[PDB]
Amino acid sequence: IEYPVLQKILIGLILGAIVGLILGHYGYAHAVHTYVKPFGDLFVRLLKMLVMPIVFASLVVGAASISPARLGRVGVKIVVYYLLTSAFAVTLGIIMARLFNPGAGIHLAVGGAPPLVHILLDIVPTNPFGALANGQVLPTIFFAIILGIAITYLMNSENEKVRKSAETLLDAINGLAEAMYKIVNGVMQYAPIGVFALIAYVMAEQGVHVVGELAKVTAAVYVGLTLQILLVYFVLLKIYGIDPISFIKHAKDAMLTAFVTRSSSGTLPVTMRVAKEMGISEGIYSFTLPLGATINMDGTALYQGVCTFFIANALGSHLTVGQQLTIVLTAVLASIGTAGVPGAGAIMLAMVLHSVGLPLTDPNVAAAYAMILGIDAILDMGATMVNVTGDLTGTAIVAKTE
Amino acid sequence: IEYPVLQKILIGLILGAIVGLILGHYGYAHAVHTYVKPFGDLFVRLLKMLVMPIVFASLVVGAASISPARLGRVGVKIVVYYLLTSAFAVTLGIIMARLFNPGAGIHLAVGGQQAPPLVHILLDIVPTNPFGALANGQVLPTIFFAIILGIAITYLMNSENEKVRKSAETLLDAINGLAEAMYKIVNGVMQYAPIGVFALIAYVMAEQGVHVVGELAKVTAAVYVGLTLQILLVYFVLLKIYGIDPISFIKHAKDAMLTAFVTRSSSGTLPVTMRVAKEMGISEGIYSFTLPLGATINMDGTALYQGVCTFFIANALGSHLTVGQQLTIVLTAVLASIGTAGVPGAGAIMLAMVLHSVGLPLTDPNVAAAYAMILGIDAILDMGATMVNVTGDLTGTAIVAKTE
């Protein structure tokens, strides 16, 4: 139950990727799935477990921070933060989708409803207890904020049974909040097993596919986001003090979980614990790391920039070069929010085709789309890991302001 | 309601193929479907209409032929006929699938590397209610009844009673009244065949023509010339070798092939297919039992389409395909549905079913990807495969006929 720290993770990752990529090439991809996968799950399981308490609890406490600003500000900022990162991510994806040209081997050309208001009203839960119980991040967010603001106001009550109990609750809640961070490390001790087993399977069952013209989308994603980290985030970390390499130092574990869990929200326990140990206050990170996981577009903007190209160019089309954006922007904007779920990228890509006019019925549209689906998991890992890097970057910059 | 004969069809076919292929390239493939298709259907409608009477009626009469042999023989022959044509079709498909090599642009490899009873389909041949049989479609149980009825009528005529010998005639005549009546309609329909043909391969070229491009087109080559080579090298070799004049055959079988190609439906063309065997001069005692039992037992098409398409997939997922061990898979495909190859789109189904057997299931999103390309070209690869099946049906008939 001992041994080296987060190199033990990197020992799992590289050793897994190799043993999986090998094992699926020799076809046992299924056998890997029935023997290895469940240790990879048990990791995501234990992380998921925490996500609800660790968010709800932390954010009642995170409304002990100055309410009118802080939770009125920052929200204004971190929104405008993602605007100016997603903007850069879009043009970094398009200019990666021209650079690499994934549409040469195919080459096979075939011709050719959200209300918002009834999703805005969904933010406000009608039963917070249910909210928590039955998953749900973004209504639990809204409650916790409204609770901790209410508690704040109870402490300034001239009565002192009230001022009394007010404390009791908030403390007891912080008991939980803290308790969970304690577990998040208990889990992390199983993270090398979890990582090894996860990208063992994910490399067996979709690695072999990363070959040929399919691989030419994986290039423009993986180096396209590698360039989002270096050229857009570090440029923003450099320009706001906080030291770029000391950042990766601290954010090591949240990125290696985001990459492997492939789930933005499913890593928030680790994501948040890195912001504690980094030294941001709960009053910021408890509201910008969850509202990040669901509002962050850096990933989808960069994956449906190069994948949008791949399809438009594989059915042998111009793609209105430089009018890529018209489609890529409209994709992001169709689900500005709720990009946290794994596999979500594939869904919007399909949904865009409904808008493009090329419906998934056209058996060659469906053919090209199915190739992306044999590679989506690899393209999802990188997109989430660059999302949760972008989440902390957004946090640590706004934090070191307000 | 007048004008030139079957050139009017060829005027529809070439003019349609051009106007459709053009119209779908400019995207109106849907608009072609909502305006043109329904005149193309109305042709297949009217033909379908006849298929039940014209088979049932014709085959009761076709048991006026000498029963113990003729319907005991020929059946033995025409079975063994298709054995030796399908054998040749298999090796003509494989040796077309190597010749053209459809698996170069993809090239996109995914690992892997990895139920019919028959007896409960044999017992389905015997209907349990002939009336229903007829009513609710069903060719191959209506076949079995009609044969059993006309044999029974034959035996009633040799009855020493002469009310019996009397009514026996009445029925069989009245039935031949129908049988004939239908051939009369089959020309009434044919006068609408140029409109039908134009409208059908107008749409079929709009909605799947544009796809016949690149590596997809390299399967259409090895099908269309692969079956063009079945006609010339296998059927004419058998027509030459059995008297019946090869070019005088196409003369007579012109209309049955241009319907089979455009209706894409083996059984859906039997009215025309049969009328060509009347006007060719075979007896009902043969053609009424070898053209329907053909439409459902003929494999010349599927053997040649799932020879080159089986390759395309095995080779597009970048596999050896065990060259020369193609047959192992191609034979087992044909043999999985020896029968019931008559339905349109059937070829696609077995191709999928083979992958279940190969070990590469349709779930594997690149298996499903390559398969989906074939599905964007299936209709074009179906027209040719049915037209060469119904050419092989009449060839089988006219050769066995000119024997027994």
Image (cartoon, coloured by chain):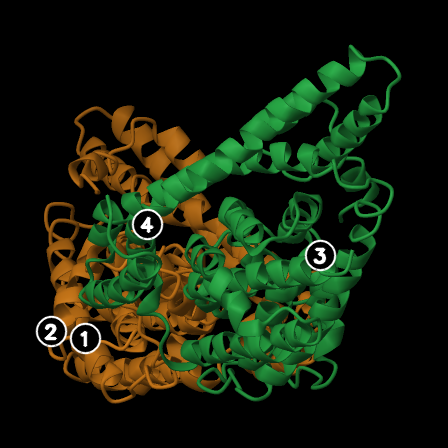
Chain colours: A orange, B green
- Which circle, 2 or 4, is nearer the viewer? 4
Residues beneath discs 2 and 1 located on the same chain: yes
Residue ID for mark 3: B401
Q: Which residue is mark 2?
A: A323
Q: Is residue B95 above or below residue A58?
A: below
Residue on which disc 1 sits: A319
Q: Amino acid at mark 4?
A: Gly
Instruction: Provide the secondary structure element on which disc 3 rests.
Output: helix
Name which residue type carries label 3.
Answer: Ala
Amino acid type shown at disc 2: Gln
| Residue A364 as seen in the image, left or right of residue B2 | right
Query: Is residue B280 placed above or below B49 in the rendered structure?
Result: below
Q: Quadrant of the N terminus of chain A?
A: bottom right
Tag 1 and tag 3 share a subunit: no
Separation (CA) of disc 2 from disc 3: 67 Å
- Answer with mark 4 or mark 3, whichever residue precedes in sequence: 4
Q: State the residue in front, A172 or A384.
A: A384
Q: Which residue is mark 4?
A: B196
Marks 1 and 3 sit apart, C-alpha to C-alpha, by 61 Å
Q: Is residue B81 above or below residue B241?
A: above
Q: Are marks 1 and 4 on the same chain?
A: no
In the rendered image, residues at marks 4 and 3 fall on the same chain: yes
Distance between mark 1 and mark 4 Cα atoms: 38 Å
**Image x and y of residue A9, in percent:** 56, 77
Give the residue at x 37% y 73%: B212
Q: Going by the picture, which residue comes out furthest to the top?
A: B163
